[PDB]
Structures are given as C-alpha cells and as structure tokens.
Amino acid sequence: IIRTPETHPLTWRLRDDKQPVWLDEYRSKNGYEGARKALTGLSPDEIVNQVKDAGLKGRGGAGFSTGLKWSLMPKDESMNIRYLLCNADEMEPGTYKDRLLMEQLPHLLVEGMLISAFALKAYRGYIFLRGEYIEAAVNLRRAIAEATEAGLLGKNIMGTGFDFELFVHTGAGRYICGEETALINSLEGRRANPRSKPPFPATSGAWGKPTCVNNVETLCNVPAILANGVEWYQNISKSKDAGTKLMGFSGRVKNPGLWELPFGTTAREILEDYAGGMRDGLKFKAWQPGGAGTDFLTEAHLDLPMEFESIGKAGSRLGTALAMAVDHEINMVSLVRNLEEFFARESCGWCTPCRDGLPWSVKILRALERGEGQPGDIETLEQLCRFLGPGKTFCAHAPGAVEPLQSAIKYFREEFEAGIKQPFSNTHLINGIQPNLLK
Amino acid sequence: AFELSAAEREAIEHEMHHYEDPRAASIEALKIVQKQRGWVPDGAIHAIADVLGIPASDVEGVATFYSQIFRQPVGRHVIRYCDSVVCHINGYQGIQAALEKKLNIKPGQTTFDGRFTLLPTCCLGNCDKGPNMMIDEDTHAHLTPEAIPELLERYK
Amino acid sequence: ATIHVDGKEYEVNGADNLLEACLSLGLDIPYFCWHPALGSVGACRQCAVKQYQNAEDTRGRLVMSCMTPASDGTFISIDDEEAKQFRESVVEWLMTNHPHDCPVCEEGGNCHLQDMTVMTGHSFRRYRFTKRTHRNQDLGPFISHEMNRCIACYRCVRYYKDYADGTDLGVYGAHDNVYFGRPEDGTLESEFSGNLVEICPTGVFTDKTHSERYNRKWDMQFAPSI
Amino acid sequence: VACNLCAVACPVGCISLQKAETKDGRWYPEFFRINFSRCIFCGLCEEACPTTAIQLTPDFEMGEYKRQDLVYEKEDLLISGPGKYPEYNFYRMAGMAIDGKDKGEAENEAKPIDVKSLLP
Amino acid sequence: ELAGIKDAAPDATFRIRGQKLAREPHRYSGRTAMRANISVHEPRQPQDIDTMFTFSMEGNNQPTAHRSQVPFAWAPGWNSPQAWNKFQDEVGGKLRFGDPGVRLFETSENGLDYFTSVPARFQPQDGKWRIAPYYHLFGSDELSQRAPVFQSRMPQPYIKLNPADAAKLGVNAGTRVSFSYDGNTVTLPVEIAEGLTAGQVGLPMGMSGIAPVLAGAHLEDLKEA
Ligand SMILES: NC(=O)C1=CN([C@@H]2O[C@H](COP(=O)(O)OP(=O)(O)OC[C@H]3O[C@@H](n4cnc5c(N)ncnc54)[C@H](O)[C@@H]3O)[C@@H](O)[C@H]2O)C=CC1
Ligand SMILES: Cc1cc2nc3c(=O)[nH]c(=O)nc-3n(C[C@H](O)[C@H](O)[C@H](O)COP(=O)(O)O)c2cc1C
Ligand code: SF4
Ligand code: SF4
Ligand code: SF4
Ligand code: SF4
Ligand code: SF4
Ligand code: FES
Ligand code: FES
C-alpha cells in the first residue's frame, strides 16, 4: 500500500515510526497551503460554496452535508459572535479513527478548524476532546502553540485581519457528550443532555450563539479540498459519496487496523486485502459496519460497497465505517448483552424509553445468557426495538442502541431461543387467594 | 473543612477566562480538584460553586453526571479496563479475571492498601489493539492475563 | 389554525403546542413532563400521538404533542393503535422500578401517575426483574422526600430552578440512577418550595404538614377561600 | 396501614379511621371504627384491602341490646393473628422503609446505588 | 366605595340547574361512621344558609358548570391537580366562566400632583438607633407564626448591627445586647449585617415582642448586657 497525496489526502504525511508531524515537517509537505489560499484569496461565502460543491459529508457517522450545515448559519451581521466546535469525543465502541488523526497529525486538524472558522466567521473554536486521549491532548496543545507562534492562530492571522482563538476542552467521560447538542451543553459546563432540534445549533447553539459542530475527520478533510481544489475531490472516486473515508476492520482478524479508502470499496476488500481475513481457526459469522450502534450484517452482505446508501438499503448504517468482525466462537446473545449494557449505562437519563427500556433489555439478555429466559422475552426485545426507534426517544442514542439487538434477533434468532428454558413466572403464590389462571 | 489551594484557584480562574460564561469551567474545575487530590470531596462542590458563581446543585449535578469525576475516594492508581464490544471479542474477560485475582477486589472497589482502584470503562478508542486498559494516564494495549501481574507492579 | 384529530375538525391557536391545544378541547392525552406554567421539554415521551401530513396519509409517525406546534392543516390521531401501544409502553417502563407504595403514599387518590397508568390501560405487569431504589433526604419541615416514586419527569427541577429561581434543588447522577433533590440534607430555601407537592406528579415531594394528619382527597371537605 | 381504601369502597360508609405513623415510619390506624348496625356484610372492604388487614370471618352471632354497642372500635376488631390469609405481609412488598426493613430489602428490590458511586 | 363586594360572588340563592355547589367529592366516605362514637344516630348535614355551597357531596362540581367559585378540581380520569385543566377555558389560561373576584375601583381619569415633601438624608446621631425593619416570610405574620410547624422554620430572634456600630459598642457576633423601647428592656443576640447602614439596628418585625409598628422608630440605651 502506497500513499500519494492525490489518493490519500488524510494519511500520506503519516510517518513510518508513528511519530507526530510537527509544524516545520507539516509545512514541508504542503502544510497550511489550503489555509493560505482560503484566508488570502477567498471570501467565507465562496469557501462554504466550495465545500458544498465538493460534496463533503459528515464523517461523524450521519453523513450530513458539511457545506449545507455551514450555509445554515444566520446571514445577519448583528450576530458577530460565532463558534466552531470540533467533536473529538469519539466514544462509539469500535471507533479509533480520530485518535489516529489527532495523535500524529494535529496540524491537519488545526488547519481544518482555521479554514472552517474563517468560512463560518467563527471568532472562537473549541476542540471537545475526550479525557482518555492524553496523547491527542498533548499533541493538539503543542500544535496550537506552534501555530500561534508562527502567526497561524490568534490575532491578525496571515495579515488578513481575521481573529481566531483555538481552545482544547478535555472531557470527563460520557458517551452522550459526543451528541452535538449534548456536546454543546457539556461545553457550557452543564449536564450533557441533548437538546431538541429545531432550533439547530447553526442558529442558536453554544451560549445561544450560532455554532457549527463538525467531526475531526470532516475538518481534516477540508484543507485538502481548499489546497487541491473541488475538482480533485470530486474525482477521487466514482461514487455518490465524494472523497476518502477512514475505513477499517477490527476484532480477531489477521491485521486489525485503519486505512484511508475511497467510498464504494466493498467490505470484503477491507476484510481480506487490508485486514488479512479472519484469524486462523476462526470462521466469519457476522460484522457490524459502522460501530456499536449499527445493525449486524452477515457474510452475504460482505460484497457491498461501503457507502451510506448501499449499507442503508441492506438494513444497516455506514456509521463510522470502522467495521467489526464477529467470528463463530462468539455467542451473539453475550455480544448483544455487552452492547446493551454499554448503551443502557451510557443513557443520559433524560427520556423514558432509553433510560427505562434499555435496562429491561439488559436484564432480559442477562437471563438469556444464563439460560433463565422465559417465554415472551424475545417478543419483549422486539417490541423494545420497535418502540425505541427514531422519533420515539429524545435523541438518537437509543435507536442506535436497538439496531444491533434487532439485527441479531433477525439473523441469529436460534441463539436467543436457546436461552428460554424456564416457564414464565411473575407472581408468587399467596395463600388464601386463588389466582386468575389465564388460558 | 475544604479550602481550595492557590494553584487550584488560579487554574480555575485561568480556565474561566477561556469562555464567555464561567459556568463552562465547571467540568475542568472538578478535574483540577480531582487531579490535585485524587477525587472531588464534598466541600469541593461548594468551593467550586463559590468560585464560579453557580449553585452547588449545578456543580454536584455535573460531578455526578460524568463518570470520570470521582465523588468517592479512590486508590493511588485507577485501573480502567475496557469492557466494550471489540475488547469483549478480543477477550477482556480474561484480563478482568486476572486483575481481580491479582488485586483481590471487585470492579468499583479499592484495594485495602489504597494502591489500586479497579474500574470498568467504556471503549477507549483503541479497538484494533485490544484488549485495552488504562492506568492513571497510560493506556496499555494487547493485554494478556499473564502480563497483568508484571504490568501492575510498575505502579507503586 | 384548523387541526384534525381522529377525523374531527377543530379550531385552535396556532401558537400553541398540540398537547395544550388538544387538552383545551377536552381530549385526553397522557402527559408527565409538560406543565402549563413551565413549557414543553419532551422528556417523558408520554404524550405521543400519530401525525399525518395529509388527509390521504395512512402511515403516519409518532410525535410528541407537547413538542409539536398546532399549526394549520396538521392531522393527528390520539386513538391510533401504535400511539396507544406506545403510551402504554411508556407507562409500563415507568412502572418497572416504581415501588409498591400506593397504600402508604400520600399521593394516592391525588396522583397523576396513578391516573395516567389507568388512562393508558396498563394493568398487567410482565417485568419480572429488580426495581431500583434510592435513599431519601431530609428537606425540612414542609416537604417530605421519597425518591423511590420518581419517574424522572424533571418537573421539580424545571419549576424550582427555571421558574422559581431556586438554587438548592437539582438533578444528580445518570442513566437510570437520576436523583432529584438537594446536594445534601437541609431545608429547601425557596419561599415557593411548597408548590413542588402539586408540581411533582408522584409522591416524591409531599406535604409533610398534611402527612402528620393524613387523609385522602376523596375524604376531604373543601371550600373556595382566600 | 390506614390507607382508607376500605372506607371509601364501603357503599354504606360505615367505616371510619385515621392514619397515624410510628417513629420508624410505618403507617397504622390511630382509630378504626365500624358501625355494624349499618354494615351489610357485603365484603367489599375486604376485597378492596391491599394488605389483607380487614377480613370478614365466619361468625354471625352479633346481636346486641343497645345499638350504640354495635359501634366496634379498633379494640374490638384487631385480632391476634393473620386470619384467613396466613402469610401475606404488605410491608415486605412496599418500597417505604420501616423498622427492620431498609431501602432495597423489599421483594424484587435492588440495593440503592448512590449517585456518587464510581461505577459508570 | 365598597359597593363592588356584592359581585365578588353570587348570593346564597345561586344554583347550578337547581342544585347547590358541593363542598366534598362524590366519593366522600364514612358518613354513617365518622360521628358514630358520639352517637349512632346520624344527624342532618349542617345547613349553609349563608352561601351557595352545601356541606355535603349532594351538589354540583362539574367542570362545565356555569360558576366561578370552584372548591376543588376533579374530573373522571383526572384525580390530581391536573384536573384543573378541565375547569379552564384553555389550559394555563382563565377559569372557563371567568376568574372569581372583582376590582373595587377603576383607573382614575386624572392623577395626583407631585409630592414635594422630599426628606433630608439619614443622619446617625449618638445614643439613638433607627429601627430598620427586617421581615420574614416565616414569622412576620401573626396568625401563621402562631402555627407550630413554623417554629422550626422561623429564625432565632436577633438584632442586626453594622460592623462599625458593633465595633463602637464593643460587641461581637452572637453577644446579647439590651435595649429599652417604651419601658421594655429586652435582650437580643447580635448578628452582624454588612449591608445595613450605620446608625441603624435591624429588628425582626412581627415576632414575639417586636411589633411591626417599631419600623422606623428609634432606640435608646443600646448596650451590651
Ligand atoms: N463516536 C462517534 O463517531 C459516534 C457517531 N455516531 C453517529 O451519529 C449519527 C447520529 O447523529 P445525529 O447527530 O443524531 O444525526 P443527524 O442526522 O440528526 O444529524 C447529523 C448532523 O447534521 C445536522 N443536521 C441534520 N439535519 C439538519 C437540519 N435539518 N438542519 C440543520 N442541521 C441538520 C445536525 O446538526 C448534525 O450536526 C449516527 O449515524 C451514528 O453513526 C453515533 C454515536 C457515536
Ligand atoms: C449518542 C450519540 C453520540 C455521538 N457521538 C459522537 C462522537 O463522539 N463524535 C462525533 O463526531 N459525532 C458523534 N455523534 C454524531 C453527532 O451528533 C454529530 O452528527 C457530529 O458530531 C457532527 O456531525 P458531522 O458528522 O457532520 O461532523 C453522536 C451522535 C449520537 C446520537
Ligand atoms: S435517548 Fe433519551 S435518555 Fe437516552 S441518551 Fe438520548 S435523550 Fe438521553
Ligand atoms: S406516587 Fe402514585 S403510583 Fe407511586 S406509590 Fe404514590 S400513589 Fe402509587
Ligand atoms: S421528583 Fe417528581 S417532579 Fe421531580 S422528576 Fe421525579 S417525578 Fe418528576
Ligand atoms: S362488609 Fe360492611 S363495612 Fe365492609 S364494605 Fe360492606 S357494608 Fe361496608
Ligand atoms: S383495613 Fe385495609 S383497606 Fe382499610 S385502611 Fe387498613 S389497609 Fe387500607
Ligand atoms: S472496544 Fe475496547 S478500546 Fe474500543
Ligand atoms: S408531556 Fe410531552 S414528552 Fe412529556
């Protein structure tokens, strides 16, 4: 695998010894060139239009158009206080892309935030980084100091009169803080409950001001667009999703890892050519395409292009595009129990279906794993999947929670019925009172 | 009787400068107190609330919301083993069993000499190198149950 | 604004949400977290109704009536099968941890949670696992605290903090262990803390002065007074 | 537990009681009076009782000379055993804490978890 | 000038379709037992010749009844305080047939003149202490301070002092000082008030021994005793 700047815009400046690339080395391999072009030759409106015509979608997992999200900021000049937030939370199980991006290429993220903040006219930027990424925090703070020293951040950046302060906000460990409105609440020093939309953060976000929240990888995608042009970015691949995505496969494969690939490469290409296939003595059973909140898929879906639309039609989600392989030795009930335990304990507690229905599924799956399941348990799980879907809950944490459960029941129902061994009993006998025996 | 030190108070005010609302420094104020003293004691809630000008109920709601802000005393070193799905596939259960056998405690407990606090944590974002765990600021990957007693011995 | 509810045309205020518009018309939608004086937040998810964009739409989508404007041309169904099943499921989820406390609870016969449990038609328990529990706090001479009965509707904190500007009540903890109360034991310092006993839809916050000589609401002789 | 369900369920209205509380917090009737000159022995109070406290028993010989003596107070009603239902204990099911039964000790109850607990 | 009190409520002959307004819910219990220890003969329900309400459940409390005086809110299926929804025109608005009560006077067409009696500034003078009123929600009202549940909520009696005046008297926080007002030498522990202007002592109005008429009055012989 070779990495040219044309085919690997995100990972071609990665070093072989996995060491971080600092300002002199980054600028040696065409660093802050897109920032220079954007800040010295383009108005913010045509930068937003350039990103929109590049077709850059959200790399956080939902695939929303970045230029469309940037264009939804208010047009009035009265609202001159604006915020750009980098979602460096990355708490989805199976996701390790942003750690790679921030640990050894922090200046790529800094340049992306600088370009995006100039496009959004955002006077301030915050990197909402998870607390467990100590190396990313150290490298990002060092790169911010280096960019401030060499006039790339602060007051009068490149002589253009544009002021931009970049801060790093380290988190305190909750998965719901990655949700963008809960991210905004956590940045304001509150409990990280999400907020209802509309209004979207573009009109009233952080402290009521116009705010744009973007993933690490999205902001890392913008400087190559600004440096090499829109036409280069459109012709990376012949797919509906433009550009390159950090894809990977993890879990008992020969070479678990992370590779920058164009959209539309099949999951079998990632699994066999890049991940090396399954390990010796292990047979492929299932896979999750885009993190812990996506539906399981079988071996028949391995010949599917890794795009939002193609994975969407197969009853799953592209997600973070960091797939996880499940071998034959893994009990699916135990796997879904582990997933649901994570999802139930990471509930923010705002809304009833997630907060009180995910623990019910956890207890049912614990009983099924122990062989103490009772009739009606699987139907209860299916009803929980139906009633925790999109729109039933306040945010999208619970639909993502119930995607693997419903897909595992759909594809591996025989393992769930194997846990139902005891008859259903909810009552004890009360002496003197004859029960109402249903038929 | 809790009193914020001069270093703690100056760090909290310096973080108050970073936002347009001093309430936005509550998480990092709790983290500053935790970094200095291992955890956030009860009087620290009122001290931080007094510094930031927000109610103590808001500070305590923040402190008890976030899992890495400790409102109970912990050991000198906090072990945080990942119990999420990829490390479950990669066999974190053997790692948890080895840690429990070496430390003779349960998750959420602290060893009787106050050295180690064992805690499950969500995914550490290192799933290609699992199973993973985190001692205080150091992440250890590619864990095996045999390397656990040796690797725990370097934290005194 | 003209709305349609279950095939019936109604004239409502377009500046109102659907829950307050439908309750003003005499229709019954169960609700917990909304209050007329506090606004809508969409927490409890109890007020679900099915919404249709056109009259010639049969699929629909469940929405929160408290979070949905009662604009012109909306079609909703309260008595839709999926809406009724979801509202019953929300009540059932609230019932999974609720203590077996109604005989020794001061809210009984005056309890909004009892009324909405009956209103949704949920009377059969199939949850068989453990119920979470909480310790209580001493809140002073006026308000008695029983957090086992909480449904986490956030009404108390919204009233006390946003409406009454009180500082010593809050929400603590996380997912299913959310706790509503003071940061420590002590008297509630707001001069309007007593409205919690009517704001709270359960028996968490109760009138301690009435609890000393307690009687049920049906046994009371009332009069309008000043 | 002086819950007053039997009094309101009585179609005659011949039950009158008042709630009182012990120091540990258990509810009990301060008084409990039944007008047996009014009572029709319909059994609706026993059916409405959620603790099986009030029970109609196989005894019909209640003739009296003065009908003021048909007003039975709590001293004339409370027997020294469980009656028709030998084992049911309402307080073993209730979440409310009393003496000898703390939070988390009732049936189907988990132990309380403090919000300050280190586990996620 | 009190002619508007006729319309504050309808008179005792008011009916809802011939029936009076009920004071108690329809499921009111214990009618043949609640007085049975006194006498097994049930008396008549007490009569209300004064108002339109009846001392029984044999009356009207419908949410659609044309009245303004609602003794309690109840509707079938709504037993909580949420039953007030059914009694309003719209939820959170007015009672559906008007709120009870009537204003005695309207806004006058013409106003007053400016009051030209501007007082001079406050001057502290030696040996003379101006009484600053300190009211308490729990304590300053006579009847409610008689209630036994308010005794725990009521503050301990005190006298507020400026730090400068307390230093001039040689008095710290918590020490008891005695002062005489109209032949009543009473003693009170001192609380230091930063915001109270010097030359004043703060007194809790309406408590035991501190009448609210003392607001704005003076004080003599305030000494540590
Ligand atoms: N660690 C991670 O990266 C994790 C990622 N996810 C991903 O999160 C996704 C769900 O996140 P959501 O924010 O709920 O998705 P979404 O579809 O609601 O919105 C995504 C983005 O588009 C914007 N947006 C969408 N519609 C908009 C509109 N009409 N006007 C303005 N802005 C609009 C939102 O503000 C947000 O920034 C999933 O696809 C999942 O894969 C989930 C969990 C963890
Ligand atoms: C429960 C939940 C957790 C999320 N966590 C993250 C996260 O950790 N990082 C992230 O970039 N997006 C996360 N998202 C998606 C964000 O809400 C949002 O879509 C994203 O941060 C910014 O959008 P973008 O992809 O266009 O950059 C999460 C969403 C949900 C519902
Ligand atoms: S689904 Fe509801 S309770 Fe769960 S994380 Fe989202 S808002 Fe919070
Ligand atoms: S809060 Fe309501 S439902 Fe719960 S025990 Fe009390 S009366 Fe029963
Ligand atoms: S204590 Fe009462 S008002 Fe507060 S969230 Fe719980 S049920 Fe709602
Ligand atoms: S049996 Fe007697 S006391 Fe019991 S409900 Fe019937 S009439 Fe009333
Ligand atoms: S006898 Fe039963 S129904 Fe009557 S008050 Fe006592 S516990 Fe309640
Ligand atoms: S699943 Fe353990 S590090 Fe991600
Ligand atoms: S009343 Fe609408 S969600 Fe609670």
Image (cartoon, coloured by chain):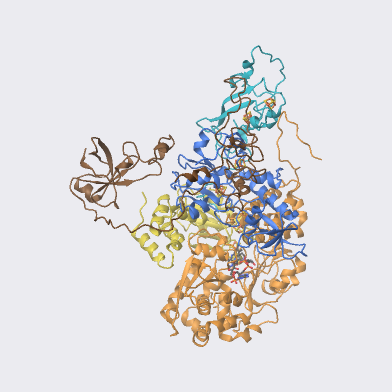
Q: Quadrant of residue A335?
A: bottom right
Residue for point 58% across, 67% down: A199
Name the outermost residue toward the bottom: A41
As displayed, is residue C79 above or below residue E70?
below
Work out whether residue A305 or residue A285 is closer to the camera in this orientation and state it: A305
In the rendered image, is residue E100 in sight?
yes
Chain in orange? A
Residue E77 vertical placement versus D13 (above, below): below
Quadrant of the rendering where the C terminus of chain E is positioned: top left
State which chain is coloured brown: E
Say which of A80 and A112 sits in front.
Answer: A80
Task: Supply the letter of whichever chain is cyan.
Answer: D
Quadrant of the rendered structure where residue C20 is?
Answer: bottom right
| Rendering colour (chain B) | yellow
Residue E111 horizontal side relative to residue A311, left or right: left
Q: Indicate the colour of chain C.
A: blue
Number of numbered discs present?
0
Nearest to the observer: residue C129 or residue E185? E185
Residue C97 in view of the camera: no
Q: Ligand 1, what quadrant?
A: bottom right
Q: In front here: D114 or A185?
A: A185
Q: Is residue A339 above or below residue A156?
A: above
Q: Which percent across, then down, holds residue C226?
A: 49, 42
Q: Position of residue A118 (x, y in %)?
A: 50, 79
Q: Position of residue A90 (x, y in %)?
A: 57, 66
- Residue D44 image-quadrant placement: top right
Looking at the picture, how far across and down is residue C67, in whole percent? 62, 59
**Residue lying at the far left of the rendered structure:** E126
Furthest residue in direction right, as rendered: A439
